[PDB]
Amino acid sequence: MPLRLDIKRKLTARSDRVKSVDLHPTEPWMLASLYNGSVCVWNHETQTLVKTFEVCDLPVRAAKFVARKNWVVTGADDMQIRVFNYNTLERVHMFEAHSDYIRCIAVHPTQPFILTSSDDMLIKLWDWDKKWSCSQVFEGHTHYVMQIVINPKDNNQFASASLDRTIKVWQLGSSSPNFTLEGHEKGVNCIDYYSGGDKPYLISGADDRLVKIWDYQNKTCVQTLEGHAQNVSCASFHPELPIIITGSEDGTVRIWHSSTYRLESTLNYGMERVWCVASLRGSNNVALGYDEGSIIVKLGREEPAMSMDANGKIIWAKHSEVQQANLKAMGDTEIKDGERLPLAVKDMGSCEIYPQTIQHNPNGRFVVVCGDGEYIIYTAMALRNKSFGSAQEFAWAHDSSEYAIRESNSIVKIFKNFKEKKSFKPDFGAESIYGGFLLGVRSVNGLAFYDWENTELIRRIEIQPKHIFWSDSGELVCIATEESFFILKYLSEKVLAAQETHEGVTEDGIEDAFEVLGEIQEIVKTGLWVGDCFIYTSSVNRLNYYVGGEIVTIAHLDRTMYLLGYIPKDNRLYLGDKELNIVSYSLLVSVLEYQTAVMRRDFS
Amino acid sequence: ATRQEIFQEQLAAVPEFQGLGPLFKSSPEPVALTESETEYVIRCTKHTFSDHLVFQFDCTNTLNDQTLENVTVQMEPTEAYEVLSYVPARSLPYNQPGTCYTLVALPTEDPTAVACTFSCVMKFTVKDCDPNTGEIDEEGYEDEYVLEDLEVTVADHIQKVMKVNFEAAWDEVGDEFEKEETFTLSTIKTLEEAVGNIVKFLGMHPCERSDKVPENKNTHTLLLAGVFRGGHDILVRSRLLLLDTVTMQVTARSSEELPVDIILASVG
Amino acid sequence: LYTVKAILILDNDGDRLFAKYYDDTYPSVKEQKAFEKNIFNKTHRTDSEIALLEGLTVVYKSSIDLYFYVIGSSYENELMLMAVLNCLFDSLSQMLRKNVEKRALLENMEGLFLAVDEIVDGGVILESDPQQVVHRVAL
Amino acid sequence: AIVDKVPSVSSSALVSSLHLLKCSFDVVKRWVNEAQEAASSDNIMVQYHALGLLYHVRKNDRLAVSKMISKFTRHGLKSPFAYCMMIRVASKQLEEEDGSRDSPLFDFIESCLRNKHEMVVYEAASAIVNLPGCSAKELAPAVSVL
């Protein structure tokens, strides 16, 4: 299945062998330790350095942020532990815990702890509240302690990896593991945990190119995986998607689906080997140290697929990667604007294709959903497949009765009820296609207007946008185009005549179609037509509607979000997160209308 | 007091009426008011009486999901009828006809008053089923689904005929009644389009020996017949004339006022 | 697709010592037996390419001294069915490396039972590849 | 079970389900997804088994199937047997006049025709019993061959 997916080369740096990486969540800062011996902390967002520290100039193996603590923890292989309060980078304390090359720290978050593993064949626990006591020493070694990871799930219990190939999982009441298991046929480089609390897997790494999965509760190697191209420097659990990240001793990325387990893809930033990895716990952004540098990639959608019937059911599907099996919500009750609400429970669905679009039929009704690149349309109540095919790009014929498609070539065919509509058949350069009332083909950094029955270049305007929302009846239409935004009139009659006369301009489209009413310089988180009113979000998180020459913020939102739906009757807006708590604020549409009409001189 | 009269009677067992009459003619076509195997499936049949028209609604509340309850039928009209009432099929379980009705009284002597399209919205309180062994309880919540239009025809009402007195009647109907429309046809010189709308829309007989055309023919007249509801007749003469353009005289003459205006429209 | 209505393992002497009625529709053990009497007997000591009883397919391998049977509906493909019919037939044969007799059965009663379960389990044929099988099992 | 490579057990798993279908099996339905992960198959018999289930499943459903067809359409078949159920099937929509014999059916047919799975050829042949000879001609070759 396709990479029609989010992969972003989020941030880059080319550097050295950056051994270690550690994440500051609480503010998405990242800490990295180098084979240089200098460590740096960056705000990636603008490729800006939050702080750098020369902790040692010997390669600095281990790093943590202690967020709770508000301090940042550092260690270099002067075998000393140096502390900074990250709240400057003011350096708090130093002392010598482990006297050999200190490989890893694992931390109890709940409980005030710093766990360390070091090459001394020792794991020591030190207590920060006790002011770096060596509270306890965990031993049962056979070699250098290469890695420690805390099962944070049960913080409390943790697992250890060594290249003598074995793994000890421990209980506090075992300053030794509970047991050791004889994992590798190589060495166990690494041990990692399974994001879910529900089930339990570890992945452990080797360059032997074999992966074993283990279920702790049973205590099995669930299974052992092969296929590989080169010594897997690392392989990781995708915590967002069910995929397997494989990494190599050459810095090869191979992905196997942690569901298909089919090689979904190979990527080369041959920046050489997977030294480190660290992942967003919000499960979406990840960074790995490579030799030639490091790269960070951004990998997410911002939504599920759902569309809401104005009775009041936003039927979404899935949750985040859960089966689609879950749609419904007519609710049953009422409560205060600020306060929160209850859902119903009765799934339908359990599709396979993984979507990223939902769009309702124009009457809510028929949704066409695309995923895996093909479109299943559902008969919804029916839970029937209304229909399917493979896309590239789309417009419903807004009317609620036809649809258009952009074939994964790029040349148009349109179908109304599986009949191609060729009365209209430009196939010009595009960019994207827009439907609605009036046909857009967005092409050649222009947006070009077309008929609905034959094509006509109605107009072309200056540039290309990103999105269109049309007023409801089409009329005044709203196009979202980065920061900036415009509101327009489309004037029919001219066309009728002009057309009759035929002789026109269409390079530009015909200058005798549309008019440019006014423009707001705008940034949109999400946006809305209330009729022709543009009620909109801004990504600056004020919910405003541009009204009357005025834009007013009804309210400003946490941070910005998704517009649940205003079921007008109720006159309220349901606001929507993506975490399935709905908030509602009533307006009263009439008020707007009242305003609309009166200005129009419909005072009465 | 047609086949359709039997239906006037069939309808009669109900007593919530707000007028009926005797059925005149019935529907030239039953309309599925919910398309092909919907969440709920409707086929509808429309019945005309000399006084009222009843739309009685035939059906299989489809999904075993549902039984629809608190059911009534909205109709909202454009070209006249006095709207007396909208009918509720008290309950409709899955795969099952039940009856709901909507009722109107038919104005007859007005120009524009019995052909109508009515707008439909289904309302119900929607209740879920267990088909194994169910439950039927007072609670359950409404949602409403928009239903299909009803259009009323000039053939749900008419008996197509041959005249009591054509010669005379033919003229006569002119006498009192007659409205006209002329078109001059310059891009196509064919009746046929017209023909598709007229034999078929009116449901009347082309004639007075002036019907027949082979896969071609030089000239054509349909002087055509049937009687409209409310008793009085609706009469049409279509002289289609071919010079070689077609220019044509459509006459509607009627023994009822509402039909002359109507025929000219209705035929389309 | 649940092909075995039933399966029977039979004497020359027109009796059945194994049958697993994949599905019953006329009851009893008994009722099966009467049927045997007609059918087997009649057929006895001679087989068919095809044989039918009333729109049902009649299937089965023989030995000089022994009878094998499968029943399905004659409403469907000879070949596969045969293939199967054999598949069993061979497998066991191969397996056995011997012609079953009356002897065979007493010679080891267990093996039948065991056998019986593996391919078909009440009705459908799960198991097969007889050599495979043969190897596959031995325990 | 669903996931394991040695089919057998997986196969073992399947049959049970049926009874569970007896009992019920609907929840089994929920599982369609697994089917898909499974849908990739490479053992013949096995290839066969999956479909049997599937059909049942979609057979409560025309539609998908139509897509299924497509699903196989890209596809040929491993543990044949699969061909055969599918035939009955493939016809079975068509049968009622699942429209076009012409482009789809025919595709199937040339293929069907072609095989040394003589039975398959037959399978098609037997059904098409058409009094006028829908396309009388071809049938005779098949026949000759018969």
Image (cartoon, rainbow, N blue to C red):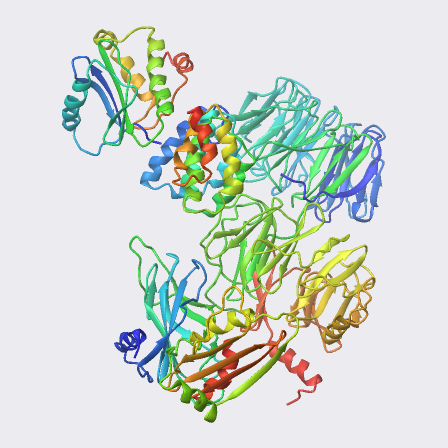
- Above or below — where is A283 with respect to C92? below
Residue at 52% from the left image edge and 40% from the top image edge: D104
Quarter of the image for the N terminus of chain A: give it.
top right
- Above or below — where is A218 with respect to A440? above
The part of the image, by quadrant, that contains residue A56 is: top right
Does any portion of residue A405 appear in the rendered image?
yes
Frontmost residue, B257 versus D62: B257
Name the spot of residue C108 as percent of width and height, x first: 26, 9
Q: In this view, does C113 lie to the left or right of C95?
A: left
Task: Count how many numbered circles sit on residues in the image.
Answer: 0
Name the spot of residue B64 as percent of width and height, x first: 37, 56
Quarter of the image for the C terminus of chain A: give it.
bottom right
Name the spot of residue C119 as percent of width and height, x first: 35, 21
Residue at 46% from the left image edge and 27% from the top image edge: D80
Frontmost residue, A539 versus B68: B68
- Above or below — where is A45 with respect to A249? below
Does any portion of residue D82 appear in the rendered image?
no
Frontmost residue, C19 versus A350: C19
Q: In this view, does A248 lie to the left or right of B63?
A: right
Q: In this view, does A75 lie to the left or right of A312?
A: right
